[PDB]
Image (spheres, coloured by chain):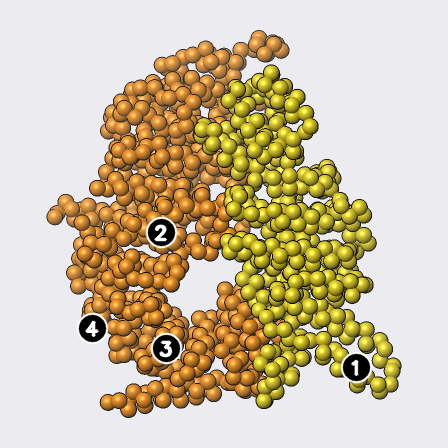
Chain colours: A orange, B yellow
Amino acid sequence: MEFINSFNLVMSNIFDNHNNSSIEFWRICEQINYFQNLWFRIHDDLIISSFKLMGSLARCNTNEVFNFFAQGSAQFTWAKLFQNFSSYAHALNSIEFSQSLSEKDSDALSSIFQLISRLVESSMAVGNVFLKIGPLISLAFQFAVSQVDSKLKSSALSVITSYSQYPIYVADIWRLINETNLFNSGLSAIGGLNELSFTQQSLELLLQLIQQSSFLFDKSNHYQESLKLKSYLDSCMDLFNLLNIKSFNTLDEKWKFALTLMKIFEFSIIQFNQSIQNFQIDKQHPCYQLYIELNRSQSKKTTLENIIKIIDYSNDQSILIQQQIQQQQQQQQQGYNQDSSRVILNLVFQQLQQQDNDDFNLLVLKCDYSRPIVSIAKLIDHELPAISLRAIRLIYSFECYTHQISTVFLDSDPNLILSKFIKMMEFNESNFEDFSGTNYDQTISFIRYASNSVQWTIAQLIMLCLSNISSGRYTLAHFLLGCSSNLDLSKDFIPNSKSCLTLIIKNVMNSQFVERYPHLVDCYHEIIWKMSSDPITWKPMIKYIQEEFPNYYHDSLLILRNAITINGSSERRTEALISSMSWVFKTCSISIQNSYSIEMKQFLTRLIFPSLMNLNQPSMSPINILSLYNTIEFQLPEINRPRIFSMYPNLIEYFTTNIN
Amino acid sequence: MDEEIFDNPIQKLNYNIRTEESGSLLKYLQSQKSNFTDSKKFISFKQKGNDSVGIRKEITQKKSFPLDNGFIGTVADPFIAIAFQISDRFNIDEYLACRILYSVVDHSTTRDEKELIELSEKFIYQNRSCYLQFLREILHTLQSRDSVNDINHSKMKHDILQSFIGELISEQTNDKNIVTILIKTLEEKVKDMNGTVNPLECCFRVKECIQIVECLFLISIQFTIKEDIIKLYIRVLNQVIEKEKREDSILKKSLFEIMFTLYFTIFAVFDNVKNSQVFNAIEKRYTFNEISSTDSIENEIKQIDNQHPIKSSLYAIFNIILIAKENNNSNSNSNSNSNSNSNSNNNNNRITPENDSYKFLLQAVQTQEYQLSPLNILFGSFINILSCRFLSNLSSHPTKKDILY
C-alpha cells in the first residue's frame, strides 16, 4: 500500500493541470479493468490518494469519473458518499449541540470534497444531479463552519466556490454565507498561518461570487446586501494593507493572495464605473470606499503606497529576470507576480477611464506624478507585450492631461527612457508569419495584437504630440524624435544618433516594412510631413533628410509605387500606400521650394522629367511624372448610398462622424 | 563552425525546413554532416593551433583579421590585446577570438575590457551549443504530430530528415556515431561539471547536459538502437548517480533531471522491444529493438550502486520486460500437455517489491510535458502489472508484501 498510494499521488499531480493525456490514461485503465480492480474492494490506506487521482481526472474525464461512482459496482458510490458526509455532519452538529474526526478522515473527506468540487468545475449537469442525491451545499457549509481541520474547511468551501460559478445558486449561497456569518472568520486579518488556506479559499469564493452577482451592487432592492458586500470589501482592503506584514509559506502563496485581492478590486471598480450615470455618483455604493482608498493623497495611506511598491518591484523583477533568464528553469513561479502587475496596470487605466471622458470634464466645468509615470515608463520594454502596451497606453492618457511628459523625462534619466521607446521601435523581420489564415485563435491572436500594437501606439503618441502643437512648444513627440534637449526647436538634429526619427526613416526605406505595415508607414510619413511643414522645424528636418538620407524622395516613391503595383492587395492596403504617397510629394515639394540641391537636380532631370538624350550613357518602368500619375488610378469608386439610411433616414447625422 | 556560428544556422535550418525545396534541404543536411560526424566540433570551437606563436605576430604586424565576405577588420592594439586575452582565457584560435570580440563590439554599447570579456564569455558559452540545438530542433520536427501536419504536404522533407539522422545512427565506426558522440560528450560535460569554479560556465554546461539527454531521448523514441548503446546508457546513468552523490544541493536538481531523462531514455529503448516501433536506420523500415544478450544488460543494471533507488526500479522494469517477452514465447508452444503448474513459482519470486525503488519513479515525474506520451506508455504497461498481480493478491489480513504493494 506504500507503492499504490505513491503511484496514485503522482498520477494526480499530472492530470490536475486540465491535461488531455488523462483521456488516453482513462481508456487504458478501462481496457486493463484497473479502476474496477482498485475500487471493487479498496483498502483503507489507499482511499485518500485514489480520491485525489479521481479529483484530478475529473477535470477532463468529468462524465466517466461521475459514471464510475454512479454504476454501483464499486465499494464507494455517490449516494453512499453522501450518506457518509451526512453521518459525519450530524455527528459534528450533535457534538456542538451537546455543549449548549481523525487525520485520515480529514484528508479523505477533503479529497472526496475536492473530487465533488471538480465534478462541478467541469459540469453544471453533474452538480444538477448531486443536489438531487442530497443537500450538498448545506453539508459543505456545516463542514466549513464546525470545529474541524483548516484543510477540510477549505475543501468544503471549494465545493461552495464551484456551485457559485453558476448564478442560479449564487443567491442561496450568499444567503447561507450571511446566515452562517462565514466571511466574518474567512476574511479575518487576525487568522494565522494554519488559516491561510481557508482565507485564500474565502477570497476566491468572494471573487467568484461578485463575478456572478450584479445584485450585490444594487441599492433599490438589495440595500440589505450591498451593505454586507462593503463589510467584506473594507476587510479585503486591510488584508491588502497587511500584505507586506502577514506571513506566507512561499512567495507563490503571497502572489496568489495578492492576485485574488487585486482581481476583487479590479472587478469592484468595473462594477463602480458601470454604476455612475448622468453625474450621479451614489455615495452609498459598496465600492465608493475602495474608490476613496485608491484615489487618495498607518494602514489608511498604505493602499496606493503598496500598489506603487508592486510597480517598483515589477521593475526590480524585470531587471532580475532579464539577468536570470541566463539560468532560470523557473518560469512557473513568475506568473503570479506578472499577472498581479498586469491587473495593477488594468486598474490604474480604469481610474483614468473616468477622466478620459467628456462627462467628467463637463462636470469640472461646474464644480508628484513623475515617479509613478517613470516607474511605468521603465516597463515600456517589458518581456510581456501585454504589460509593455499597458505602460505605453497609460503614458498616452497621462500626456493628454499634462503635455509635460517631455519635462518629466528630462527631470529623470532621458537616456534610459528614450532607449526603451527605441528598443520597441526597432524592426525584427523574424517575428513574422502571415495573417492570411482564416482560423483566428483569440489566444495566439491576442499575443500578436499585443506585439504589433506597441509600434502603432508609439507612432500615435508621437502623432498626438505633433497635432497638438501650439507653435514653438517642445513636446513628447520632439523628445522621442530627438529634437534638441535645449527646448529650442530651430536647432539641427544630431547625425548618426538613435532617436525614433532615425528609426522612422530607416523603417520607411525597408520595403518589407512597407509591405507588412502600410498604415504604420502612412502614419510615419505624416510624422515626416509635419516635421517638414511646421514653420520652425522644417529647416532642421529637411537639412537632416539631405545630410543622412539624400535618396529619400526616390527610394520612398520606388518602394510605395512597387507596393501599390502588387495586385491582390486589398482597398485598405492601397488606401494607406496612396495616402503615404501624398505625404512624400508634399515633403519633396517643400524641399524643392526652399532647399534645392544637386541631388534634387539629378532626381528631377534623370527620373521625374527624363530628357531623351541621357538614355545613351552606359557610364554610371521608371518613375517619371506620367508613370507616377497613373499609379494613383483616377477611377474613383462610385460610392453607393448605405441601405441603413433607407431604414433610418431620421438618424443619418447620428450614424455619421465628420473627420474634420 | 568557427565561421558558421555567425551565420545563425538555427534560423537557416528552420528556413530549410519551412520555405526551402526538398532538393535544397538535402544539400544543406549533407554538408552539415561534417559537423555532426566529428565529436570535437559538435559542442566545442577551434581550439588553439600549434603556431599561435606565428598567428599572434601576423595579427600584431597586419593590425587586422579576416571577417566574412572577404572583409579585413582593421583593429587597434587594445582590441588585439583583448582578443588575445579571450583566446588565452578559453584556449581558442586567435582569428575566431577577433571575430567574437568584433561581434560583441557591434552588438553592444559597452567599452570597459571586462564588459567585452563577459559578453564574449556568454557568446562563447551559449553559441558553442549550435549543433546540439540544430540536432534538437530536427528531432522535435520528427516528434511533434503538429508540424508533421504542415510537413505532410511536403512529406519528402520528413523522409529526408529521418534518413539523415538514420545515416548518423547507422554509421559503423562507433566513435563517429551520433548516439556515441552524445554519450561521450555527456560523460565529460557531467564529469567536470562544478559550480564552485565558474558558476556561469556550469549553468551553460547544465543546459548542454539536459539538451544532450533530450536529443538521446528523442532518438530513442524515433530510431532503433544497437544493443551495446543500451549498455552505455546504463553506464552513463551510473556516472550521473556517482556525480549526484558528490556535488552540493544546488546541482542536485539539474543532475536529477539529467538522471531521470536518461532513465526514461532506457525505458523508451525497452518499450520498443515489444509494444512501440521505431525507424530501423539500417533496413529503412519500422521495427522493434532486439535484445539478444539479456544477461549482459542485467549485469550492467547490477553494476549500478546498491544505495540508489534507480537500481531496484530499473531492475523491477527489466524483470517486467523479461516476463513480458517470456509471456509471448509461451503461446506458440500451446500444443503441450498438462505440466505447466511447477514454473509459476519462479516468475513470482522475480518480483520482490524493494520499497523505495518506485519512490524515485514518483519524485522524478515532476518534469517537462514532451515526456507525457512516453509517460502514458510507461503507465499503461505499469497498470497491467498493478491490475494483474498486485490488486489481485491484496489479502484481508495484510502481510509485509501487502503493506508494501
- The lab-note entry on whether marks 1 and 3 share a chain reads no
Amino acid under label 4? Gln
| Among the two numbered marks 3 and 2 on one chain, the one whose residue lies closer to the N terminus | 3
Q: Residue placed farthest to the left in the image?
A: A367
Q: Chain of mark 1?
A: B
Judge depth for marks 4 and 2 and give the one in front. 2
Q: CA distance from mark 1 to mark 3?
A: 52 Å
Residue A184, visible in the rendered structure: yes
Give me the residue at 38% from left, 17% from top. A543
Mark carried by residue A149: 3
Q: CA distance from mark 1 to mark 2?
A: 67 Å
Amino acid under label 3? Asp
Tell which of A507 and B230 is nearer to you: B230
Residue corresponding to mark 1? B343
Tell which of A90 and B86 is nearer to you: B86
Residue corresponding to mark 2? A341
Amino acid under label 2? Ser
Neighbour tally class for label 4: few under 14, some 14-19, many 20 plus, Cα within 10 Å? few
Residue A655, visible in the rendered structure: no
Contact between marks 4 and 2 (CB within 8 A): the answer is no
Q: Work out whether A581 lies above or below A202.
A: above
Neighbour tally class for label 2: few under 14, some 14-19, many 20 plus, Cα within 10 Å? many
Amino acid under label 1? Asn
Instruction: Give residue A231's quadrant in the image.
Output: bottom left
**Where does the image place residue A323, in percent across and percent down from the top left?**
45, 43
